[PDB]
Amino acid sequence: GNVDLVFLFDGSMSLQPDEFQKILDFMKDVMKKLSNTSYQFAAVQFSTSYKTEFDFSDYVKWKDPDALLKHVKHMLLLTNTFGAINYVATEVFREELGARPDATKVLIIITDGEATDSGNIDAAKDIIRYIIGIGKHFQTKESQETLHKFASKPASEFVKILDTFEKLKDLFTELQKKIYVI
Ligand SMILES: CC[C@H](C)C(=O)O[C@H]1C[C@@H](C)C=C2C=C[C@H](C)[C@H](CC[C@H]3C[C@@H](O)CC(=O)N3Cc3ccc4c(CO)c(OC)ccc4c3)[C@H]21
Ligand SMILES: [Mg+2]
Image 1 (tube, rainbow, N blue to C red):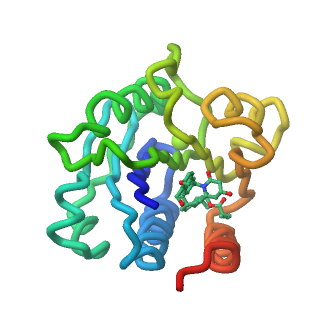
Image 2 (tube, rainbow, N blue to C red):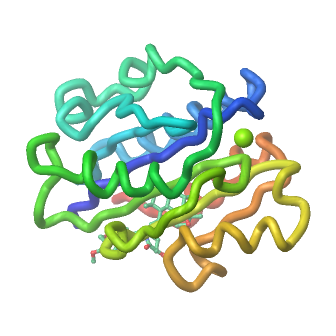
């Protein structure tokens, strides 16, 4: 079916350059895998503030993950997840930017820390939300549970916790096994 998917990725100061690049490579792999489907993509970096790295219209003209993500600069600031989700819901899912009104709305959030802001995400309730929490800031189950509020229910489907950035390759292998394009 028609899916408008947005990647919302953390550019916080905690990320080393190879870790940040692993996030970027995961996004490129997913998009490569789903080229030729009727998925459309956008990507937003968040840290303290928010930047649309590419929107749906951009993806439809270029259709090239390497080109679309070539000029990403790592922000290196905080983790304002509440505001970032609201940015996606109000600034990214818009017909003017290539969003399709018939499409299922999916958001994938990739983060390595707890949120530094406060808010609510009512404006994003019609969006299916996955969150991928990576690394040492999610060793404890308290910290993992802070992510449940951002994800769709049940957290058992929509919250993924990865202990290292190397495990993003494993997560992609699971996607390759479960999604089947004919
Ligand atoms: C599928 C198994 C992998 C491990 C996974 O969870 O993928 C998630 C998380 C992350 C690793 C990467 C992803 C990359 C792309 C997909 C969006 C994928 C989830 C796909 C699908 C898995 C399903 O079990 C739960 C769900 O809500 N969706 C999203 C989705 C996709 C299409 C939908 C369509 C059109 O086919 C609908 O129209 C009938 C309705 C809902 C849809 C939901 C998502
Ligand atoms: Mg961080």
